[PDB]
Amino acid sequence: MKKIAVLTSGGDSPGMNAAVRAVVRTAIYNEIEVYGVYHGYQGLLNDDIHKLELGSVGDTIQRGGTFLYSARCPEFKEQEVRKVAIENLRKRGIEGLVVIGGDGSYRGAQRISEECKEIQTIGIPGTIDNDINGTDFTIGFDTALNTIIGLVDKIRDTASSHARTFIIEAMGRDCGDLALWAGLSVGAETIVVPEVKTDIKEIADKIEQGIKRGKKHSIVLVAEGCMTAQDCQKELSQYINVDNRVSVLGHVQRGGSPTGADRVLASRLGGYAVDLLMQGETAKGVGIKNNKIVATSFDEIFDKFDYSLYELANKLSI
Amino acid sequence: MKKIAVLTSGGDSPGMNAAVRAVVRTAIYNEIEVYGVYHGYQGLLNDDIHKLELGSVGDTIQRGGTFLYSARCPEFKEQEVRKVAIENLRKRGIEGLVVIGGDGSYRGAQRISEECKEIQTIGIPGTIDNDINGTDFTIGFDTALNTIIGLVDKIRDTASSHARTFIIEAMGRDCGDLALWAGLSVGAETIVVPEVKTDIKEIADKIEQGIKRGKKHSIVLVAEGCMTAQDCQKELSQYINVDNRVSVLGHVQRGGSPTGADRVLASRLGGYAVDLLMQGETAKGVGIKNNKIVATSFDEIFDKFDYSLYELANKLSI
């Protein structure tokens, strides 16, 4: 192990740069040369690979996004396309590749490992979802969680006193953790997640039953996995009156400076990814499980939801 | 268990109100009456106890500080004084007391348990330190961590291009986690903590050795446990020239809206504290250990430092 590459792939998340920075510095510290792959797996084909120095990742820990870019490369689902990528790395003496992104990102990294016993592959969970196996938390969750708090607080502050219903869409893809954690945190009355059977009757039954009962605003956080915010405001008229702010947060959730939580988390897993390459390991996803940094096979990673915390969230809304 | 009291005690931390809110709501949910003790243990003597309704803790999750106040009550170190406190609770039918604060706060709660087998006591770690046993993290750490990031980012942005040294004092009392976590996160070159022998020669040896080597600013984070920021700027002239921003962050670190991390954490432990009272337990501190919510005896609580992460922090500064 003397030449490592690194890419970022899929929807961007806060701390991606922190993660890269950690890989670069750790590797270089261990007298390993490091190559920045630009535009995700697209760049891996386009041969958009470039050596990185210590200074190449100066003034990035705090950076939102990814400075190596990310692409969508659906064509990478094809052995024959992948053969080109593999060569681009194979021609430059790169024996290891690190990959920062979703469980999607991980896929192609597993492919490369299977399809080339030379190139070691390692996966780092740079994503907002929280939806990766073998990690309690992913890089971007905490930041996203705080973005939503922040956005929610704004809507409150910029709204008039009439609208007493904020139907807020959180970006979980198929995992309700963000919505749960953000719901709890903003004192949402109702939280709508894939993992719990959503009783819209009961939900309006509780807005009606506490807002002609004299509070200031009620908020409904919604996991995008469950439904759109427009779908829920439709679904909620069909019992009671609410036609008030339906906020579709979206991609702002992916921007912004990572929080402390993600900077450290990213840094730790970027370092650990490099160690594992030095220790000759391959095709694993790193993460944090039971406050221990760990590695988990892409096998196990492809082959959960705190209903207690959900139940608690509800216990805490009057 | 039908009457519970709750207080906040010691230096205030973000999420204290969240914690209270959780106790109140959970208790009431379980048809337990709940009494707000005002001004810490002082109020416990002064008999400044007052029933709390669901609405008494509306619009508090996000609140910085504590709305029941906190006092310093050194006199509480005296059996005879405590006898009064105990009676105040004992006269109103309160069989359980919940206490949100430092390991100091916990002390007197253990006393009360020993000194009155009627009153169940439970401790919740509302503090910035991280310095309580049987919890990986305390309520306020994450917020503090992010405050420091934020403060550090400001100083940067409001400084001129000359001063290339920011000697920043972080509030850990005797524990270097904040300084470590904040140092890492702001890309500090040097981190000064109680737990590592601090080689001031080597430190300036590295500012001198990278700043006439052409970077923009270097930052030194300092655990207040180790030394003052003024002491370190003195200690650092005594080899090399630096007479640049020595920022003494202080009590701002204790203000501000808890982050998501602490709102959830607080909420979870406030709920769990109430459960444990219902389950007839006593004289335990709750916390989160290995991503499991747990309880730990005040015994064990009175009878650690990731040098690997410290070592990593350094690996990542050029």
Image (tube, coloured by chain):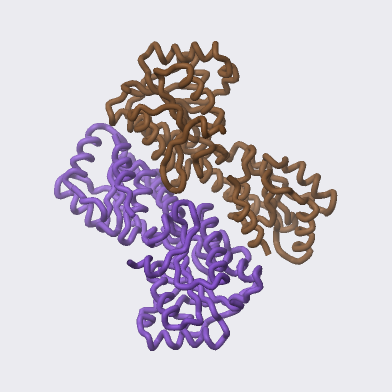
Chain colours: A purple, B brown
Displayed quadrant of residue A135: bottom left
Q: Provide residue A302's location: percent of width, then percent of height.
A: 35, 67
Q: Provide residue B178's location: percent of width, then percent of height.
A: 59, 46
Q: Nearer the viewer, residue B39 or B113?
A: B113
Q: Provide residue B300's location: percent of width, then percent of height.
A: 52, 34
Image quadrant in which the C terminus of chain B is located? bottom right
Tell me which residue sits at (53%, 67%) in the image: A273
Q: Provide residue B217's location: percent of width, then percent of height.
A: 70, 58
Q: Nearer the viewer, residue A290 or B214?
A: A290
Viewer can see residue A252: no
Callout count: 0
Tell me: residue A256, above or below residue B134: below
Image quadrant in which the N terminus of chain B is located? top left
Which residue ends up furthest to the right in the rendered image? B238
Q: Nearer the viewer, residue B64 or B292?
A: B292
Tell me: residue A92, above or below residue A256: below
Tell me: residue B177, above or below residue B312: above
Tell me which residue sits at (55%, 23%) in the image: B71
Displayed quadrant of residue A29: bottom right
Tell me which residue sits at (54%, 11%) in the image: B80
Viewer can see residue A201: yes
Direction from residue A226 to residue A115 in the image, left or right: right
Direction from residue B158 to residue B84 in the image, left or right: left
